[PDB]
Length: 123
Length: 121
RNA sequence: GGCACAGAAGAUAUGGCUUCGUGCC
Image (cartoon, rainbow over all chains, first blue to last red; front, side, top):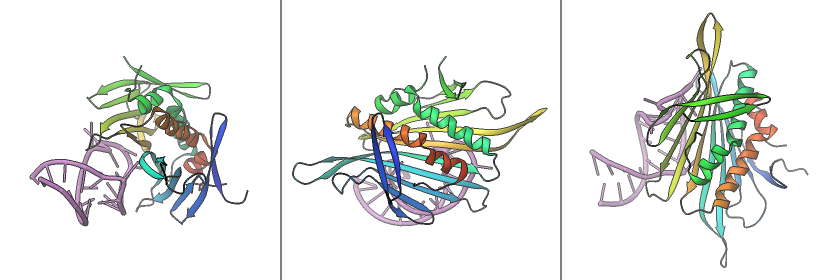
């Protein structure tokens, strides 16, 4: 209850990423299940540019593939990172619109097909 | 012609392909002035080793104020970089897809992008 | 020379870029 988390729902299941590191710049959430190697991990950071005219949100989801013939071992890692440029004097509506448009984009079957089957966008 | 349709509430935005190369495509919302049209750029490439693919997706949103003559004030962007291992299971790829679908839909992520509120509750 | 790197920093984004690091021919 008291560790901070982000909870991801995939259909009927939910997957809780527990915060394992927090610094002024950066945050790391990891899923507390399974082998200690290759746990699902979310790295997130917020940063201003030198001019203080824009922000950069970085989010990075690392999904490792662990095989366990004896003791566990990460075979490979697949990653989906995000890089969001927010302008400091932007209207809130402009940021909500970017968010709304991306939530829709990622939710499309076309983007599912691209990532899962390498099928080009456009129908 | 080729399109992708995005749905916000009861509204839709139709992005239409205006360009393609062997490994890149550019979609715009072909509505209104040419100034500041919503744009999606999509790329697919291989590893140096040919053991992985990188998918790049980038949404550029200009802020246009139309007081007679349109002008871009600023542009905000949300880009994605996806690393897909070549020999991987469809299940593992679909899982990463679903986890990210869910990640972006969280109100924590909205709070981050819209209000700069750090993640974790 | 050429190439690799989910190495680091910068960039409101042809961000298919720049610089720096490390490694392979």
